[PDB]
Amino acid sequence: TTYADFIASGRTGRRNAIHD
Amino acid sequence: QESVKEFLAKAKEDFLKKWENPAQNTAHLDQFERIKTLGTGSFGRVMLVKHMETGNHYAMKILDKQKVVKLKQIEHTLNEKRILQAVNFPFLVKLEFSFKDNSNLYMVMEYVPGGEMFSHLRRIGRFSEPHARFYAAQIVLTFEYLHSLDLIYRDLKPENLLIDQQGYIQVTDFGFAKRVKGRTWTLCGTPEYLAPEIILSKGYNKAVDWWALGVLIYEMAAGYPPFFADQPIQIYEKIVSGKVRFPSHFSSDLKDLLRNLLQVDLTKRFGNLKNGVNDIKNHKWFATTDWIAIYQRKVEAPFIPKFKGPGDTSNFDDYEEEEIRVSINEKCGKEFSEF
Ligand SMILES: CC1(C)CCN(c2ccc(O)c(C(=O)c3ccc(C(=O)N[C@@H]4CCCNC[C@H]4NC(=O)c4ccncc4)cc3)c2)CC1
C-alpha cells in the first residue's frame, strides 16, 4: 500500500530544509 | 472584496514602517529563565523561557553567530528577524523581543503550547477533510497576507505549523523567506515540498507557496505526502514527473483542488492566475469555509490541545539540553550589526 511505502521510505520523521 | 483591499493596504503600511526601521535590542538574556528545549535547528534551538519580571512564558530562539557564519547564512538569519519583527497577522507567531550578545542572536516570541502539527498528524495518522480544510484555510489567508507584502515563505510543512490554545495555527521559522516582487533562483525548501521550478533550477515566484499548500493539504488528508522516496534525488524525480495518485477516500472536490495546486506548469497553477488567490478561496472544496470567520478565529477548532496552565510543555517532545555559553569576546560584530 502507499502507506506501507511511506513507512519504508525512512522519511516519516521531521524533515530538514536543504540548500547548495 | 473592497474590504479585503482596504485591509491589505493598511497591513502594508504597518509592515513597511517596521520593515524600514526595525526594532533592536529590546531585552536581555538575564531577564529570562531557560526551562526546556522545544525544538532544534542548524544554529541553535527554541526554548521555553519565563520572563522573570512578569512571570510570562515565551519561546526563545537562540542562534550561535559563529555557526551561522560557518555555514554562510548571515543574510538569511538577519532577514528572519527583520521579517518577524515587521509582520502582524493572526496566524503568524508574534515576536516579543530580540537582542544579541557576544555569542548569540535571540528572538523571543509567543509560546505556542499545542505543539507542532507534525506531532498531531503522525499521532492520529491523517486528518478528516473538514479538519484538514480548517487548517488549510488559515494557510490560504496567511499566504494572501504574506504575498501582498511580496514575501515568499518557501518552507511550508507540518513541522513549522504550531497549534495554539484555541486550536488555530501559528506559522513559525521564517529562516529563508524572501521579500521580492518578482522572481528568485536559490535552491531552498524541504524536499517533499519543493515545486518543480525550484528543482529544475529555473526562476520562480510566490507560486511555489501555492504548490507547497497542495503538498500540505495532501499530507494532512492522506497522512503521507504526494511525493516521497528514500533519498531527496528520487523525490525530485517524482515531483518533476507531474504524476500524482490520490487515496480512494479523497473527495472529488479535494482531488480537483490538488490537481490545480500541484500543477507543474506554473502558468496554470491555482494562486498564480489572473484572479490570484480567489481561485482557491472560491473552489468547491472551500464552499463551506467562512473566510471572515476563520480570520476572526470564530470557527470551532476540530482539535483543542491539552493544556495544564502556563509553562506546560507536555505537547512537545524531549531534546538534549545544553547550557547557553556566552563568550567574553564579541563574535562577528560587524556581520550582525543590523540584528
Ligand atoms: C537550509 C539552510 C542553508 C538555510 C536556513 N537555515 C536556518 C535559517 C534560520 C534559522 O533560524 C536557522 C536555525 O538555526 C533554527 C534554529 C532553531 C529552530 C527551531 O528550533 N525551530 C522549532 C523546531 C523546528 C521546526 N519548526 C518549529 C520551531 N518551533 C517554534 O518556532 C516554536 C515557537 C513557539 N512555540 C513553540 C515552538 C529552527 C531553525 C536555520 C539552516 C540552513
Image (tube, coloured by chain):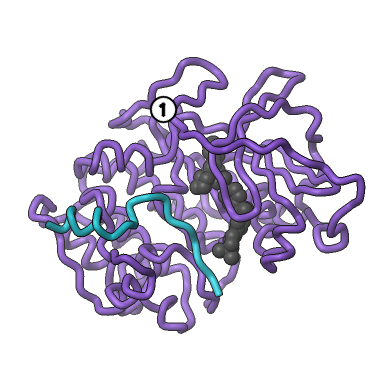
Chain colours: A cyan, B purple
Q: Residue furthest right?
A: B329
Question: Going 65% across and 62% down the picture, which residue do you hit?
Answer: B76
- Asked whether residue B268 appears in the rendered view, the answer is no
SS label for mark 1: loop
Q: Quadrant of residue B215?
A: bottom left
Q: Quadrant of residue B240?
A: bottom left
Q: Residue furthest top?
A: B309
All told, the count of numbered labels is 1
Question: Going 39% across and 22% down the picture, which residue do you hit?
Answer: B306
Question: Going 35% across and 58% down the picture, which residue do you hit?
Answer: B213
In screen coordinates, is B61 left or right of B336?
left
Q: Amino acid at mark 1?
A: Gln
Q: As displayed, is residue B153 above or below residue B108?
A: below
The image shows residue B106 at horizontal and vertical percentages of 72, 44
Q: Quadrant of residue B300?
A: top left
The image shows residue B62 at horizontal and vertical percentages of 68, 44
In screen coordinates, is B150 left or right of B143?
right
Q: As displayed, is residue B23 above or below residue A6?
A: above
Protein chain holding label 1: B
Question: Going 91% across and 50% down the picture, which residue do you hit?
Answer: B329
The image shows residue B281 at horizontal and vertical percentages of 30, 54
| Tag 1 residue | B166
The image shows residue B19 at horizontal and vertical percentages of 70, 55
- Asked whether residue B300 appears in the rendered view, the answer is yes
In screen coordinates, is B54 left or right of B338?
left
Classed neighbour count for the residue bearing mark 1: other residues with Cα under 10 Å, few (<14), some (14–19), many (≥20): some
Q: Check mark 1 vs ligand 1: CB closer than 8 Å? yes or no.
A: no
In screen coordinates, is A2 left or right of A15?
left
Q: As displayed, is residue B206 above or below residue B6?
A: below
